[PDB]
Image (cartoon, coloured by chain):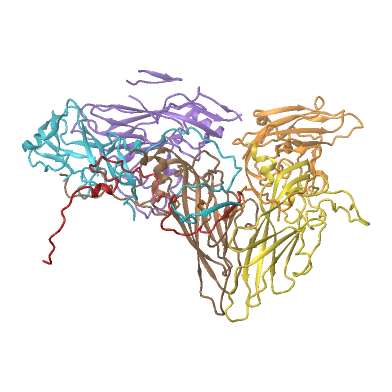
Chain colours: A purple, B brown, C yellow, D cyan, E orange, F red
Amino acid sequence: RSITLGNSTITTQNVVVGYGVWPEYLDQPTQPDVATCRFYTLESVQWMKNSAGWWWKLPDALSQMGLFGQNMQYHYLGRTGYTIHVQCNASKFHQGCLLVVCVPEAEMGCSNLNNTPEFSELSGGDSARMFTDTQVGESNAKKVQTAVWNAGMGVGVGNLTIFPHQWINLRTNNSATLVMPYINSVPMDNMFRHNNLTLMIIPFVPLNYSEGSSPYVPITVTIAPMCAEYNGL
Amino acid sequence: SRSESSIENFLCRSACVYYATYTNNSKKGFAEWVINTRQVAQLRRKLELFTYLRFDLELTFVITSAQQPSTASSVDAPVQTHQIMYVPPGGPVPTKVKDYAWQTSTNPSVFWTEGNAPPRMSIPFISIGNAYSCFYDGWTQFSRNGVYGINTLNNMGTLYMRHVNEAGQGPIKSTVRIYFKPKHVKAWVPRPPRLCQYEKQKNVNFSPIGVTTSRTDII
Amino acid sequence: SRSESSIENFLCRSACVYYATYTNNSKKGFAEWVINTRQVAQLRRKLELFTYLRFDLELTFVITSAQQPSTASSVDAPVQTHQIMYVPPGGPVPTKVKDYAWQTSTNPSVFWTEGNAPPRMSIPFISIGNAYSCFYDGWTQFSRNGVYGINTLNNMGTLYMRHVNEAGQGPIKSTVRIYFKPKHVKAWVPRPPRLCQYEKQKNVNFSPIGVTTSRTDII
Amino acid sequence: GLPVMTTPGSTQFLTSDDFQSPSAMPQFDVTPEMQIPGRVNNLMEIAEVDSVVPVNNTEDNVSSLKAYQIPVQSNSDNGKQVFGFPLQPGANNVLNRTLLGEILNYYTHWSGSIKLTFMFCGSAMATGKFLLAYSPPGAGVPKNRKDAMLGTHVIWDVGLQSSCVLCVPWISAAGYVTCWYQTNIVVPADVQSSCDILCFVSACNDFSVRMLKDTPFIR
Amino acid sequence: GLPVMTTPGSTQFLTSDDFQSPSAMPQFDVTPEMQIPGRVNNLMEIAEVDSVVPVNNTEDNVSSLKAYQIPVQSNSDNGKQVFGFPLQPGANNVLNRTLLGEILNYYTHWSGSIKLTFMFCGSAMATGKFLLAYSPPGAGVPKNRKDAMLGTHVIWDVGLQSSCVLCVPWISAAGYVTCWYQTNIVVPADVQSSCDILCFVSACNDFSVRMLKDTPFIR
Amino acid sequence: GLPVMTTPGSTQFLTSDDFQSPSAMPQFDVTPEMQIPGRVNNLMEIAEVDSVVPVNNTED
């Protein structure tokens, strides 16, 4: 409860760790931590009744987040870990269920079978891109196919529980916590042409309430890098 | 019976991945196959269960010939001989049958005549990284402009095949079936199996289909 | 990764150094290759980085035949056989296909029929001195008059190839590609790499070219 | 030399052999391994995780997220069935395309048990009771609540426990996991009544598979 | 006799094999070795020496000895660039045809550091100061003296030291080693002002190369 | 390599040989044995039992 990192504080009260490994460190690479290990809090999204889902490409959402987004421009390479805290504050009169996965190397498919989706439609700067419950027509040229039951990757969406995940059930749970180590083939990769993680949130059981309650539920995502290092003289 | 579900028992198999023909008299008849894993749709689905693989490689070629219709006058030919050149990633590439890139020193080739055992050769795990990647969420590395999701760091090379005997009396065309076999497989970070049908060889594009087959009632 | 830049890993390779044809019916059809290192321009540049080399030698011949257009009347021939004679430095030399110099006892030959493995033979380091010399600043030794820069002390011999079956019904011409491979290489006193283009096989003559490619400004 | 004798089956290509092999590129000095998280040594480590079962197919919910939800309302009937699915394998049933069912379709003979975890995704002020009956193979499906109680069953109280696990064997009429209303869903004022239920499947014990084959989910 | 069984890939010619071989001339009694000075065991012993870099190409100095000299005069401007060259490899840059760049073009992947020794070949009564800035990869070229000071740099006093060494890594916008006037060249009477500067390159640490290929400096 | 020399009768198919053989399906993990009653090790264990002799053939 009331953990602090640098000059930021959040308050919590279970934690699922990656693939059973804690994040850890390895010319000469330098290890900066005083400008990075702090809770970067993204803006909150609203879970309405006719909602479908959200996704964040993970070293893209923190590209304008202060002194972590400056090291991405100055330093050429680097590896990172993460620690994600997702929580939705709803009352005892609401009901629903959320699935919070963290997909490594989540290559997504275009709406057209002959092209590839453009850069602005995969990720935005610290703003969640959202799915839709219908099919995107093939008359469009470069857009991501965002049907929820396929999760954009051509896979069954029920089988997404093989990744490190945590269920948020509004009857008995309030928050989730994920710890993700560095998962890549090379020990240091470029942080602009590569998005090695993807945080997805998908509501299976949709939100329901009676007439009178608040017609939305805000969800708060807080990301904090852990054990980051770069390559530079 | 727990040993049959291991990674070595699941992946160390053989599969016909390529099948192409070439004749000798057409002055441009040779073969080409860029080595990848996304050729057949039955092995691509099994290697897509994991994200990072690392294996040695073992290839065997089954070459058979067939006499094309010649003109006349009692064709009688000796045994045929073939050359199977392997180009490493970042090497010269031939464009004609008579070219400098065949007679180079770096590209290791095999030579094989008919009526013998098939010509097996084995390629070790060659790359710059530490593992292969069936999936890549990003743009191409080391380039001015990059197509989405290519990952040129995994590149196993190319194969080229041609006849090395010139005979004018009889034209002979020949087929080749390349057999593919991983060895000493290590796999990391599993991944759920593909549901939708494959459409193209380059990308993971698809068309949205339902989850499973339907029934008439829940009970 | 320091072991790939060793001398053995840099030079113990294979290279097609010669390619010549010969037919049987022409009464003078045979092959000849004086063994040297200055044949191909890609191996000559690598052996010119050092001055004194000393290696064993290993050769493999890829022989293939091709039926020439005969007259008529159902040509049917048996398997062919070839003779590959190696003449040491200072030996007899044939000038016709039927000659005494083939049937001598000192010149070691191999005999080989079709449809088998290629005929490898290996020549040890033969010389009078202690090393070879790619460069020689002087006139020829042991002679009345000497051409500048020849150095007859390095002389590895000559190879000769011919058919050993006479058939009148069908003419057959055959090719041969000689593969070259050093073994147990020792190199002394390194030498800077060649910049200008090669022009002749005998000498180190050249035409003057600039140092490198130019740019538009110093800054 | 040494006298040998070739046995039958010598110069053949069996696709399922294991011999030594000549390496195409020796002296390469390949990249050493790196500790990548999450190594897969066996395929039964994939099946042990839980996955959601599409119980609610019903001919138009398969192309939506409604297939994974089981609708539970407040009704006026005295005893009523919520859902029910057989365990007959491979023939269009619900456990075919799940994460457990994709490994067991790469094999022909398999045997083990199943964990079936349910989850009540409703309000926190809602209460109720459900029966979770399991009919063994050979016995028919219960057509009534009273003889569904007389078999093996687990009565699941919602307000006390949000998730109840029902273990069951599963072998390659073969079983039913039908579920019944015991009491209605009692709810306070300004709370909705139409609650939902999810269903999870897993592998409770270690499975035993044999005789690998191809999967039928391809063209 | 003994029962054997021939495996596939038996009677093939792989060019990159290593087997035993029948010697063509046994019983020869070859010449023993002699201690010749300067034996080369590795190719990285060639790269460790220094070589002059043609910084001053400029479209008509390449066919002269003026390409190796960097002109330094006495000017009236306040802060000015002397030279500058990028470190992007292989694409017509200055370090391509040097003695270090000829070994690293026989390989595909390499990584190491560089010593860059300068030398002021001017009079003994002349004084001055120069900046030696190095821009890391990713950062742009400095367009001004003031922000060229703010990076990593070495200020080089001529009258105290005639040669200053600047170490830098070099990997297969990628870096700049630009150089700036700090003060002018102060000179006495009856001494010239137009002095020159040479540039040397070397290998500071041990390089690591892999996957040998052919060089592109041939027809 | 090693010098060998092929003897006559080498690439022949004798039907009554006993050699090694390449297995078509390795890595199969076959079913272990079960104690089934009445194992036959020799054919003379069949002949030791008694049987009735048709002494009275007599054409019908």
Compared across the picture, whether E214 is left or right of D143 comes to right
Please, is residue D219 above or below residue E183 in the view? below
Percent position (x, y) of residue B140? 51, 45
Q: Is residue B34 visible?
A: no
Percent position (x, y) of residue C134? 80, 49
Residue A53 occupies quadrant = top left
Compared across the picture, whether C100 is left or right of B107 comes to right
Percent position (x, y) of residue D195? 18, 35
Q: For the point 50% across and 36% down, which residue is it?
A: A191
Compared across the picture, whether F8 is left or right of E144 comes to left
Of residues D203 and B73, the one nearer the viewer is B73
Of residues E70 and C208, the one nearer the viewer is C208
Of residues A221 and F40, the one nearer the viewer is F40
Q: Is residue C115 visible?
A: yes
> What number of labels is visible?
0
Residue A58 occupies quadrant = top left
Q: For the point 31% across and 27% down, which residue is it?
A: A175
Please, is residue B41 above or below residue A194 in the view? below
Of residues A36 and D166, the one nearer the viewer is D166
Please, is residue E110 above or below residue A233 in the view? below
Q: For the point 70% across and 64% down, which residue is it?
A: C20
The C terminus of chain A - image quarter? top right
Residue B99 occupies quadrant = bottom right
The N terminus of chain A - image quarter? top left
**What residue occupies the far right of the structure in this picture?**
C144
Percent position (x, y) of residue E135? 65, 34
